[PDB]
Amino acid sequence: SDLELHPPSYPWSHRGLLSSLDHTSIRRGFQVYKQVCSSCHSMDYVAYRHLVGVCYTEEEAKALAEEVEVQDGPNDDGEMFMRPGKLSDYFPKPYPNPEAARAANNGALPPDLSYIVRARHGGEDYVFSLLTGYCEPPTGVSLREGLYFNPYFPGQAIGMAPPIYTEVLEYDDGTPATMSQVAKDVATFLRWASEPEHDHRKRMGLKMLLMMGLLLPLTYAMKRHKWSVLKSRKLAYRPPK
Amino acid sequence: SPTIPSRLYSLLFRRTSTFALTIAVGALFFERAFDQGADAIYEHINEGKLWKHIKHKYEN
Amino acid sequence: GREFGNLARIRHVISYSLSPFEQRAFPSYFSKGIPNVLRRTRERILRVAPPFVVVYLIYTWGNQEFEQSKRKNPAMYEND
Amino acid sequence: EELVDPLTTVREHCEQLEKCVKARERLELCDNRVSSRSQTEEDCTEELFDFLHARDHCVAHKLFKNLK
Amino acid sequence: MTNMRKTHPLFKIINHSFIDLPAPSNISSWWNFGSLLGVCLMVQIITGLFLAMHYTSDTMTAFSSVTHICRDVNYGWLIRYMHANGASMFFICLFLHVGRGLYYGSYTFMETWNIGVLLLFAVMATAFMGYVLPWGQMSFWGATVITNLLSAIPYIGTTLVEWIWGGFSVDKATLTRFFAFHFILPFIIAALAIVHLLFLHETGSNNPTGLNSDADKIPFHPYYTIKDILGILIMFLILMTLVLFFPDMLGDPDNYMPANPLNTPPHIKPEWYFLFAYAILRSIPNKLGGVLALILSILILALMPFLHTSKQRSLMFRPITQILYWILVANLLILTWIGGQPVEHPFIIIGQLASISYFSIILILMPISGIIEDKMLKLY
Ligand SMILES: CCCCCCCCCCCCCCCCCC(=O)OC[C@H](COP(=O)(O)OCCN)OC(=O)CCCCCCCCCCCCCCCCC
Ligand code: HEC
Ligand code: HEM
Ligand code: HEM
């Protein structure tokens, strides 16, 4: 069907005008991506050093980077070799090229989730509604293998199997990993991944509002000084008759 | 008894060079005070959410 | 060629002004600003507003007409 | 001791409201009409969309207070 | 001694154009807008220069360079979104400047008006190629659609489009030459703005009453200096609340995907300030008809000084033409709304009626109304 279903507005902790992101939720959503979403989706523009000072310390992010193996080279014989990862390494590819993703995902290409709440209408609301909106198809419509019904996906036939259920991973802080909690955490993490400057942007905006609230009446007062020399000027016509 | 703007004019605002000096000194002091106040407002709006609020839990 | 001194020929006109340090920058700002703004908006509201009012009506009608254009016609699938 | 998703509890609590149960009634009238006909190309995705729109609107009104 | 301000040959021009320039005392805040445009131009140039130290005009690396600017350059996201929202602010100030010129009869300064419409064409071309530059999905498909409809010219159109492309389609050569042209045109815009200021300064500015303001003129400094400073401050407030709080309310989300030639978007738009012209371009079911409709929809401002049939310059004392002017602003907003809508019912008939009404109000209704208004004052 060509009819579309808009996702609703959720009360996010960063929804407000000066409201920053909850960094524990970004840490939990990074764990959700690492354990679930990294098998199919890529994060080509995010590195491990971006996690320092946001969700993890330097040594925690160093351990996270060294858990994986990165292709590197050329060696002195001219051959490629695996090495442990470091902080300057970006997040590992699931597939070496998109045609391998097409072959491994029944013809569908799992998109790079680095701008996925910036490239979709709804933002993180759309991601939450897509992850928590898998349901049985209604009567009249039928779907084949490799397809799953999702009313928030355009066309209502998504090639992605439902990846999140109750207790799909174990959190580091002991939070109960329900489907809604895991989806909210990964939506917060994807919002941070699309907008890493978000808290700094809102702090800059707060300083800008304070500075403009200081400076606009003062510049208005200077203008009205230099113009109130003219705005009380009185004229008189005195013809000699 | 002169008032505060009158004494501010007599000591600082008359000469243009002293006007520039008090503008520069007030600029640096206002910069320090304004960054401190605006920052404190920003963590007061978003307490328990920034990295410096949850930073003590993970550092060893 | 066109500067102060040779702009216009003015005779018998007296202007009075005072120093900006002598007068207030906001002389009765609200108590005369509100009726002046009300006078200006009542002299211009009938010329300005009704085009934007009918833009609002056309916008709402077009959006709702598109929404019922995407609506399923119940007359179909009635014969069988 | 299964870990209960708060989204489910909020979902039937929101389906207890009136616009959701009216849209659900139209959905059952549609599946009664469609599933009892042999050959047709009718699909009623639109009032399933209406029911989901109302239900997830009132779910998103109050879901996030139960999530840590 | 010697007055250095009125004698030094570099300070003499600065004096005559900004300090001792006799300006009308009663010009409203609308006369700020052109100065804002100049400031916006400088802002764009400055931000553009700081985008040019990290941007690469290669189709493999353009999106990667833009993401590197947003993510790794210190405050690079700030400069990029300042550049984008400053282009939007440029077009806001440009539209209000043109509306001031239309309302107050400033088009009787014919040379200034013609240099203006040349500047408007140059700014639109610069913004189009700049929007092509990040090489997103939306940039590639907007460039493809605009050049494909430019191919409608008979007997030279396909050759001209393949010459502009440098190939069979929109490719690496198109992006690199668009980077060069988008770099070089704002300096030509600055030179044309200098010519614009000279052609205005031969005769002074217009006032909202439309009368000869020679009896009441004031120096530009300090009155319009501090007024322009206040307008600059307000425009900076709106620009920074557009950048720091709602950085994507005016852009399209599909530009954050990489350019896929295989995948077409479901709905193709230019950015919002082109949108009304796009509506006019699709109000005729003929390719040449739509192209000439767009060209005359921009060039009707150049045709405007020959349509003035009234004995009064401004619209301050002309209520019927005021009503027609606000109806013109109304259906310009309507065409802007239609241009972002897909081509089904009732958007097609609304856009056709809006384009017909736009051309009939500018061409027919305003001179007839001016004749009627002259008849009411016992002048005709
Ligand atoms: C007959 C007037 C009666 C007025 C009664 C009100 C009381 C008057 C006495 C008390 C004073 C109150 C304040 C006065 C303010 C200034 C004076 C004023 O408002 O005058 C009326 C004004 C001008 O009158 P005038 O121009 O002579 O009328 C010709 C109509 N075409 O005329 C108007 O304001 C009327 C404006 C009507 C505009 C209608 C526009 C309809 C079409 C819009 C199309 C927009 C685009 C649609 C889509 C197109 C594409 C699909
Ligand atoms: C392999 C089984 C995958 C897992 C694990 C995850 N995703 Fe995925 N995703 C996959 C495919 C094959 C597709 C494309 C399907 C199609 O029909 O296009 C997707 C798509 C997405 C999208 C994009 C939706 C859109 O409108 O384009 C998103 C936002 C998405 N997937 C999210 C997502 C998340 C957050 C995951 C971790 C829990 C995740 N996916 C895992 C394949 C797979
Ligand atoms: C000579 C000065 C200029 C230079 C060097 C310049 C350079 C650039 C560069 C490198 C980009 C790509 C980076 C990006 O994606 O933002 C860009 C984008 C852009 N430029 Fe410019 N530019 C200049 C002036 C202008 C002007 C005057 C306008 C307005 C008409 C403009 C409008 C744009 C737009 C709309 C974009 C797209 C922004 C986006 O990605 O959304 N530029 N410019
Ligand atoms: C590139 C963007 C432009 C810039 C930088 C620019 C710059 C200026 C400046 C500085 C002024 C003098 C101050 C003022 O009166 O506002 C001015 C006035 C003027 N401009 Fe422009 N302008 C631009 C676009 C245009 C366009 C597109 C037109 C034609 C529609 C135009 C026509 C005029 C006219 C007629 C005036 C005289 C104002 C009057 O006396 O009423 N300008 N412009």
Image (cartoon, coloured by chain):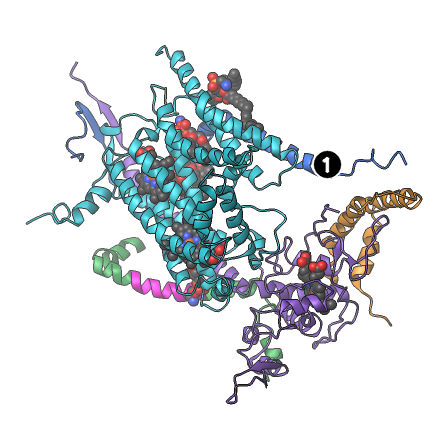
Chain colours: A purple, B green, C blue, D orange, E cyan
- The percent position of residue A167, horizontal first and vertical second, equals 78, 71
- The percent position of residue D15, horizontal first and vertical second, equals 83, 51
Return the residue found at the far left: E1
Is E329 drawn above or below residue E231 in the view shown?
A: above
- Name the residue at 57% across, 28% down: E353
Q: Is residue A239 magenta?
A: no
| Residue C7 located left or right of residue D28 | left
Queried on whether the Cβ of the residue with tag 1 lies below 8 angstroms from ligand 1, the answer reads: no
Callout 1 crowding tier (Cα within 10 Å): few <14, some 14–19, many ≥20: few
Q: Quadrant of ligand 3?
A: bottom left
Looking at the picture, tell me which residue is in the foreground, D7 or E364.
Answer: E364
- Please give the chain letter of the residue carrying mark 1: C
- Mark 1: which secondary structure? helix
Residue A186 placement: quadrant = bottom right
Looking at the picture, tell me which residue is in the foreground, A142 or E216.
Answer: A142
Main SS class of the magenta portion in the image? helix
Is C9 drawn above or below residue A158 in the view shown?
A: above
Looking at the picture, tell me which residue is in the foreground, B18 or C3.
Answer: C3
- Quickly name the residue at label 1: C68
Is C5 drawn above or below residue E39 in the view shown?
A: above
| Residue E187 located left or right of residue E358 | left
Q: Amino acid at mark 1?
A: Gln
- Name the residue at 76% across, 64% down: A161
Task: Confirm whether residue C29 shows in the render.
Answer: no
Q: Which stretch appears magenta? A: B23-35
Q: Is residue B28 magenta?
A: yes
- The percent position of residue B10, horizontal first and vertical second, equals 23, 56
- The percent position of residue A52, horizontal first and vertical second, equals 55, 76
